[PDB]
Length: 265
Length: 99
Image (tube, rainbow over all chains, first blue to last red; front, top):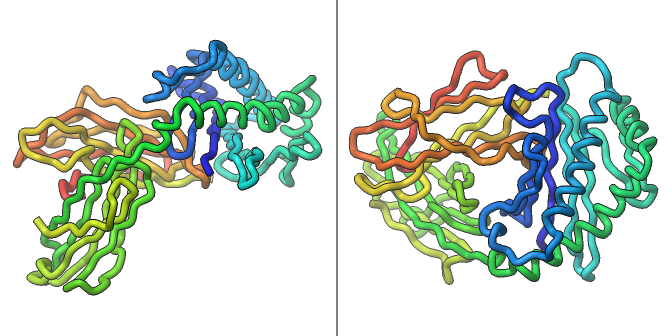
């Protein structure tokens, strides 16, 4: 089922005008929350701006993230030295098959996973000396472990359930992709065929090529977001010059009732 | 650790000459998070460019979307220019309208 996940980052020497600490919050693949240490306020994103919330919703998100801001910045002092450092955290929860919450609490230092929070013991830990140093500093801070436990075991699933109830339609959004299949010349004797899927949601999507109705492979491709949180994808196949018209592309996506055949332009 | 950015350039909607649209430059998979991105129109830096929040994927690598409103034409060429510490010089990726 659907995850609520906070992506937290601190940097020890932010570029001027940029935040030392910022957070994005995600309900599955769409962002609902933004926070940075320069504004110091948690804010809704996209359609979640229009969500009907409890009267204290966003002030409590702000309260929690200001606390995590202080912790992340304390982590650099525990390491000492010139740095620079990047500290990231992935904190959140998802509801499990029997309608209970499953927590996530992992951290990375300079792009490398190095620490987690153990919810059974209420302690941060990891193998590297940087993990031991930061964990000890956090562990020695009054109520820090307690607030981390509450955040993951109570606040997160409560928020997730509230958004499932108040924003169900936002989460069930199904926008089918606009499809195009086009060929361009390549090296001598070859063309590149590209099947492209525009402005769709959710991100799960399959593109396949057929040659005279027979399976011709997935091709090679990529995918990415648009500014509104919908998505874009393409996949490309190298084919012999003059043979392009024998090919089509098939797309599977939840916004369509059936797989859709896309013919060359 | 350092990771070099992957760069993708595509429009929000299928490109149609004379129809308003958005051009995206999606930069992902990079570390550390400091990155510089410009959209270019026939080589000239575009002034009115917005960007999403710097976020990161399950493998901790960062990603970012830059976008600008534009109206494609037959002859105008667009590109994305990216600088990052992993790059010995700025990388320029041309917009392929098919992509």
